[PDB]
Image (cartoon, rainbow, N blue to C red):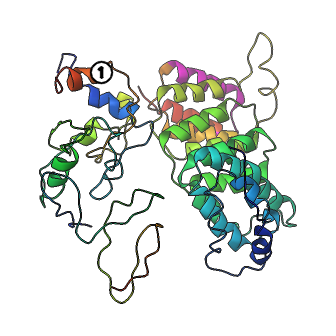
Amino acid sequence: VLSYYKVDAEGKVTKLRRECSNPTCGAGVFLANHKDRLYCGKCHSVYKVNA
Amino acid sequence: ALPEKVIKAYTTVGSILKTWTHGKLPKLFKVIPSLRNWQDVIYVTNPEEWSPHVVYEATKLFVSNLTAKESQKFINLILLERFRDNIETSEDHSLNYHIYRAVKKSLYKPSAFFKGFLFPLVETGCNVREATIAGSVLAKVSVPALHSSAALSYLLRLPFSPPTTVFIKILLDKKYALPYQTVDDCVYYFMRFRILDDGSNGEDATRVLPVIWHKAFLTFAQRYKNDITQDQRDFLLETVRQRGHKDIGPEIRRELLAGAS
Amino acid sequence: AEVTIEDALKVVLRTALVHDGLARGLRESTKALTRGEALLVVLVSSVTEANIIKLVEGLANDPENKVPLIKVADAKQLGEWAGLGKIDREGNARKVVGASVVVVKNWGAETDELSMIMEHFSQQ
């Protein structure tokens, strides 16, 4: 259930609400809405930042 | 590659794993299957002395992350031996409920399951209890056509035993429109149980045949009466008229007469 | 139709179904589209939302390698070009329901049908 691929034009996928950096896997999806507690998907490099 | 590490920290972790209550098995345990050398790492944690919650979170971790060749070695080395030890050591010789989980959680990709568990089991040391428990295992979970037909034909390439006949019945319960070579394996399987002339076919057709053969061959007569050729119908009716059951036999004859095309 | 073309994708979706690399969905076709190791990736662009259209135009036509174009629409018959059926022609009685747009990694079939519509017809 996603309509969040408003992407940049011609043509590559560079994403607002920026992605993750980890060799463990692909890490080509967003890191989006957070509120006083974060959760960066996958198992890259934690990321205990503020919201 | 054939190197390793210094610790030897999984003795301290594995001593904690023997007293583990519930939840998620710890973060130092979560890094075992990622190694190529996971086999020697897990043997430090004493896998034969676990609790079933460790069995669940562990088996959930190992099956859903190792490759099918690696999960083949995991099930072949451990879960098969843990399965037969859970049958043998238990004085009721039955399955625990908490051994009534992770196992067919692990079955949803049946390739590594069949390469690890089923194919050594039915070819070595299979009996009526493993056909009752594992017979209850095969029917409840998802399976595609290729594994059912291939493992079914692997059952049909075996000599006669009622525990194998249970698994044949369970695979005949799924009622899939089989490819014709699997159908011909079923017909060529069930033809040789009648008493032929010439010589001996060989000793398995002259022995008494239990009710499970009439139930599985009954199920094949029910679903597969409209997908077999007429010569196969006449040959299986020839098998029925020599080796039919007192009650199931004429019903198999009636369902084979009820078929067409 | 009675000639030797269009029938690659009919069979390459059987030989490439062997390796189970069919990244098929909105978010998760990008799994096989985070690299260009996929080769013959069919696409449609006509239902709703105008999003994956824009994704296919940029994953198919990036300035680097992996630049095919095989636009062919009507994904509800693309199940019929896929391998949902275990047909045995008069035997099927099976799950007829849909098997839509694929992302083909690990081809399985070797230069016989594929060069007909890819090489002979799309790339010069």
Left or right of residue B5: residue C101: left
Residue B239, picture quadrant: top right
Query: What residue sits 78% from the left and 50% below the top?
Result: B128
State the residue lying farthest toward the top. B198
Write down the region rendered in magenta. B231-248
**What type of secondary structure mainly makes up the magenta span?**
helix
Reply above or below: B14 against B209. Answer: below
Residue B167: tell me if it is visible.
Answer: no
Q: Is residue B240 magenta?
A: yes
Reply above or below: B146 against B46. Answer: above
The x, y position of residue A47, in whole percent, is 43, 76
Residue C32: tell me if it is visible.
Answer: yes
Query: What residue sits 41% from the left and 29% below the top?
Result: C108
The x, y position of residue B28, in whole percent, is 66, 70
Q: Is residue B243 magenta?
A: yes
Left or right of residue A17: residue B36: right
The x, y position of residue B185, in whole percent, is 59, 26
Reply above or below: B159 against C26. Answer: above
Crowding at label 1, few (<14), some or many (≥20) Cα neighbours within 10 Å?
Answer: some
Q: Nearer the viewer, residue B62 or B79?
A: B62
Query: What residue sits 29% from the left and 54% below the top?
Result: C25
| Label 1: element kind | loop
The x, y position of residue B95, in whole percent, is 75, 64
Residue B238, picture quadrant: top right
Subunit ID for the residue under disc 1: C
Q: Amino acid at mark 1?
A: Glu
Left or right of residue B165: residue C56: left
Which image quadrant: the N terminus of chain A?
bottom left
Query: What residue sits 61% from the left and 38% below the top?
Result: B151
Reply above or below: B111 against B156. Answer: below
Reading the image, the residue beneath label 1 is C113
Left or right of residue C56: residue B261: right
